[PDB]
Image (cartoon, rainbow, N blue to C red; front, side, top):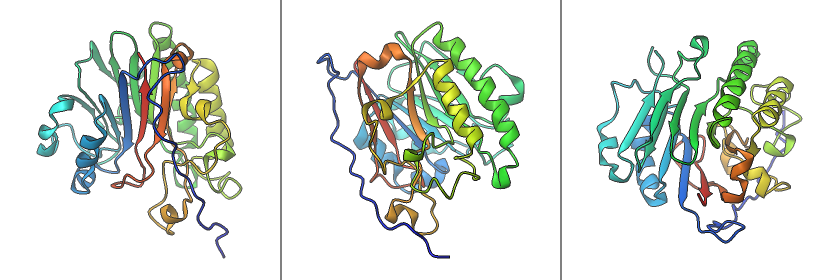
Length: 282
């Protein structure tokens, strides 16, 4: 049947590097679902990272065993503190966190054994905030994993509420849901597909309410359509901007005065997701 979507333009606004208080950004975090660490490195992802020059780089879907890291990661001197979590298994899921400065503490998982076996979460505590990066479980073809995803969602929200009770929290990564209709090009056709089910959208709303957390991009750009971070490799989707916003920076409300900008690096190639970048004046 005929596809209804042609190209929809989206030009990410210029980087706002000053907070509403006037304070210059001091922290630049980039998050990227890389669709396989080795594949992404061959597609020059590290060249892009070096130009972006973030203080912290969070990666999802590394698909790479913690004992099989590419040597090309050794040539990242500005991101020398590198932490990885991969399934306890090989070649799927997996996250990484690479940092210019050394975190006070690094932890893996959410403290719930059922949910900690698939290499999905790294927690890096710094002086003024705690950073979590996550690759949230996909609801699956035919929604066969939606029940598990709902259990994950509840355990993850409870875990994050606990962290944020002690230190301001930044959550980033691939949360595997487009929260609202503005967050994907085809809401009408996807309400029964992974990433846009009512259960997943409600889970995201529950996450924002319960921790609580604010969606940094949507806070700054509440009415901006066509801003996506993922496009299927098939069906010419990226060229038409038939996409989904699956990648987020969620922030404790106390960090909103420090929020300078939340960017979507639409033009950066190397995966079926693009990078997102957060500027904070901490």
